[PDB]
Image (cartoon, coloured by chain):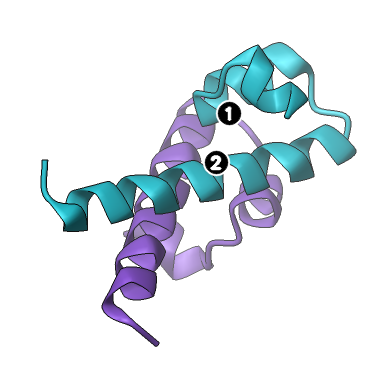
Chain colours: A cyan, B purple
């Protein structure tokens, strides 16, 4: 891919992690966080 | 800002909209979608 599409992907990953952090603090079930954000369990752990 | 940080911001906005769309289909209350994703009501409408 291009550098622009790589930078957009970094932003998507950054936003998904931030949303997941909020959901974690609000008590959302972890299986739902993974469904909504697309993140792996090791991404949630780190 | 720089072009890299603008491109990352476009990715963050794209991912927030996608997550919001999933949450909408799953019946999440709209006030919660807005809290988790940071989106405005007009961003959810469009």
Specify whether residue A13 is in view. yes
- The residue drawn where x is 34% and y is 82% is B2
Dot 1 and dot 2 within a common chain: no
Report which quarter residue A21 is drawn in.
top right
In the image, residue A40 sits, relative to residue A26, either above or below, namely above
In the image, residue A14 sits, relative to residue A31, either above or below, namely below
Question: Could you tell me residue B46's position as x and y percent?
Answer: 31, 59
- The residue drawn where x is 63% and y is 25% is A43
In the image, residue B26 sits, relative to residue A16, either above or below, namely above
- The residue drawn where x is 18% and y is 54% is A3
What chain is tagged by disc 2? A
- The residue drawn where x is 30% and y is 53% is A8
What chain is tagged by disc 1? B
Read off the residue under disc 2. A16
Q: Quadrant of the N terminus of chain A?
A: top left
Specify whether residue B17 is in view. no
Q: Nearer the viewer, residue B5 or B29?
A: B5
In the image, taking residue A2 as reference, residue B6 lies left or right, namely right
Question: Could you tell me residue B5's position as x and y percent?
Answer: 39, 72
Q: Residue furthest bottom?
A: B1
Read off the residue under disc 1. B27
Q: CA distance from mark 1 to mark 2?
A: 19 Å
| Mark in front: 1 vs 2 | 2
Q: Residue furthest front?
A: A3
């Amino acid at each position: 891919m291009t550098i622009a599409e790589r930078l957009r992907q970094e932003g998507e990953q950054s936003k998904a992690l931030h949303i997941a952090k909020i959901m974690l603090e609000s008590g959302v079930p972890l299986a739902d966080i993974m469904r909504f954000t697309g993140l792996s369990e090791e991404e949630l752990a780190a």
